[PDB]
Image (cartoon, coloured by chain):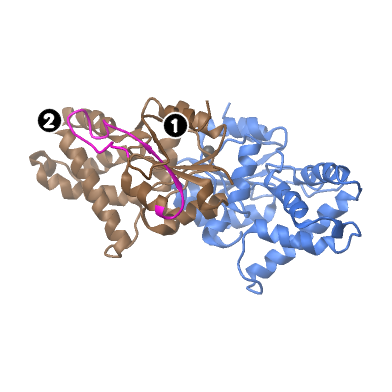
Chain colours: A blue, B brown
Amino acid sequence: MGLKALFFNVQGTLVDFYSTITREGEAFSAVRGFQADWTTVTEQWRAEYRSRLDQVIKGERPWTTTDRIYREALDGILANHPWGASLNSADRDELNSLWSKLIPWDDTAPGLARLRSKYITSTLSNGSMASVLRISKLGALPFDAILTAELVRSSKPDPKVYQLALDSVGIEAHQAMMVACHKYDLQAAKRLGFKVAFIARPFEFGPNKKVDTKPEQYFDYYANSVVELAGMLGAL
Amino acid sequence: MGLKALFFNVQGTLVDFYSTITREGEAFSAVRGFQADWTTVTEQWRAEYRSRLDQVIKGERPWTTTDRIYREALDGILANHPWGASLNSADRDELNSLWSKLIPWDDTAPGLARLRSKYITSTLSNGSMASVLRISKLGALPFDAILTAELVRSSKPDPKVYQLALDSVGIEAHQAMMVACHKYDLQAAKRLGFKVAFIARPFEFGPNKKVDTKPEQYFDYYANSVVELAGMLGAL
Ligand SMILES: [Ca+2]
């Protein structure tokens, strides 16, 4: 009746989406004969995705997978760059696939392996199952299971998403820990009886953007990396 | 558009529940001072389990976790054994827990690792997520995802379960292969457009029981082990 299972937020917490979109974006445009400010594209793409996802959650748009939202969001932001109209549909599919390739932080894979030697480990992502399984496979990120909010057609912080984790692994809330670099996610899990571990990710939005990494009173654990979290849990 | 993902039946195809039941049951019964015919127990237990899954599909029984199905099936078969009435509910709980501890065939883990190096791999099981995750973890069975019929509150051969596989991994039916040692499973998947691979398991019910390992014309592959299947798919 101690901690039995750890559940992980994927974007930010485990993978560096900023460096993926900006560096692969630059390689993508170079091969095609143009250049662009990919930091701006990345920010615009993320913001447009979140606005469309919000419309799904509010019922103003029909339900669809996060991969499709990313792909429709891409069409939207490309209309504000003069080179955007030069990308055909296959070009935009390839760019959209980067969200299924988000690279790990350099602590993520070894920390995850150590944690798995002691606990059941699983994602609990807001994204599509297809994208998350590929992120984990491409990153060689070990998990006992892949779960995402898509399996209950919802989004965090809907309690159904957290309960999906408990039901799927067969444990009670106090035996589960939510691990994230986003406080809204940990707040919701804590209110449902999960233990919570915060991983500080000071470069989540790139090298130059200040991120809120300060500790909070309700965190069970405060860590600077997945490797550090494994140490404090005695998973050596 | 080429094979992208393999989906595995787990009990029987990948893990040897007969050896697990006979070995655990033998120890279970020795400490209680009686002997049982564990070959017959295994046959009856799986048959009652399958009959109850069918009731879930037919709606004669509301969906419950497969571990509750195994537990109630055990109550049913224990009326056919004189020692069965000597087992209280806690005894029966202990015996039921073996369904999350099934031992892999010797070829399963190396074959699964080779296939994962070439394809996306996933379970697609009727067992609970909790049990199948734990079977895979205890047996060091590598997968890119753990899917079970629990995620759509049904059971194979319900078409919803095969669609769950395609939606979750994000591929089309012809890009997916169902792998099983049971023909009902491959027949249903083939009818939905999957490729299918049969793995012969002549000792699924021990050395004294005959099982159907004959090939069929609709099998895309017929193999005697997961390693042999990996050889056939160019994964070695
Ligand atoms: Ca896995």
Q: How crowded is mark 2: few (under 14 residues within 10 Å), some or many (20 or more)?
A: few
Residue of label 2: B35
As drawn, the label of residue B229 is 1
Q: What residue type is labelled 1?
A: Leu
When the figure is inspected, residue B186 is found, relative to residue B137, above or below; the finding is below
Instruction: Tell which of A217 and B90 is nearer to you.
Output: B90
- Say whether residue B192 is magenta: yes
When the figure is inspected, residue A116 is found, relative to residue B53, above or below; the finding is above
Same subunit under labels 2 and 1?
Answer: yes
Q: Give the mark, 2 or 1, whose residue is nearer the N terminus.
A: 2
Give the image location of residue A152, x and y in percent.
52, 60
As drawn, the label of residue A106 is none
Disc 2 from disc 1: Cα separation: 39 Å
Residue at (57, 43) in percent of width and height: B2
Instruction: Tell which of B11 and A126 is nearer to you.
Output: B11
- Point out the stretch of residues depicted in magenta: B191-215
Residue A232 visible within the image: no
Residue at (10, 45) in percent of width and height: B80
